[PDB]
Amino acid sequence: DVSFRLSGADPSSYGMFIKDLRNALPHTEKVYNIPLLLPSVSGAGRYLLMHLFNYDGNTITVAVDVTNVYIMGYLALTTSYFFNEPAADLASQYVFRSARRKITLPYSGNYERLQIAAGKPREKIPIGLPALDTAISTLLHYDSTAAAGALLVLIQTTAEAARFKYIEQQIQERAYRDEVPSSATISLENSWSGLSKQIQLAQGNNGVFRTPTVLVDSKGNRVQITNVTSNVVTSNIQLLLNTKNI
Ligand SMILES: *[C@@H]1O[C@H](CO)[C@@H](O[C@@H]2O[C@H](CO)[C@@H](O)[C@H](O)[C@H]2NC(C)=O)[C@H](O)[C@H]1NC(C)=O
Image (cartoon, rainbow, N blue to C red; front, side, top):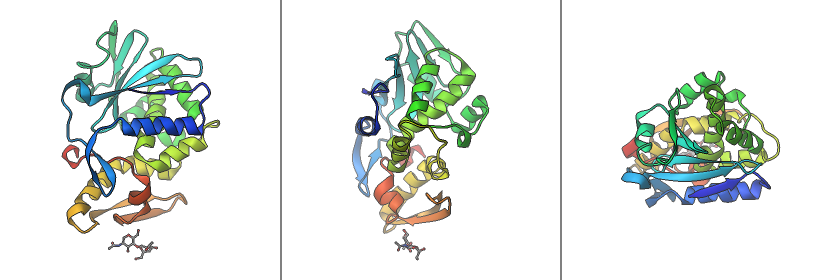
């Protein structure tokens, strides 16, 4: 398991948590020096538990699929919650079985569905460490519309930062003041599968992507990424989605 406390949190302690989160995910191989997540993991070992504490010391435990970094559901006090999708229903066979009741959220965990449920795109939802504290707090008591926005904050501040050093740094910049994600952040989120696939197809193609990936840069300028020498591959991405899952 890995844990993070919002009480006394700062950039350094958040960076330790994102470190712990990356290092909890198993890999047997690196591709261009980036850990390659596993094609599959059988049984309960396919879920990592993240214990999150709000500033008041209240806590939820979040289940994360190690193969993909997808959040499946979470436990808050004696109630478990899971997205409405087959992968989450499977997870519910393995984690938080001791919950007195299990509520299936009324949406799946994907960004499109979550934004619809929340009523706003994530371009418009501030993120940062205060937003994470609020999200933990929201999830402690069931409210499906409030929870969809809390989960957009949670997914970005924990999974997405583990995937990209740039996103981790964005959240560190927002340790004491939230701010909507940069358009570079959103682009990276939306490109993780595509980047993960192209980095792996480069292995037998001399470092060159089979199909270029388009990203927004820190300047808000669209860029083409065409090979593994890009700063996106050498510096920024931290985990690859296995192409067996793409
Ligand atoms: C591999 O990617 C690099 C970019 O990371 C390409 O070089 C850049 O692209 C053009 C020049 O061709 C310029 O706009 C950039 O300033 C270049 N940057 C650097 C640091 O060289 C390169 O062309 C790509 N190589 C292949 C084989 O696709």
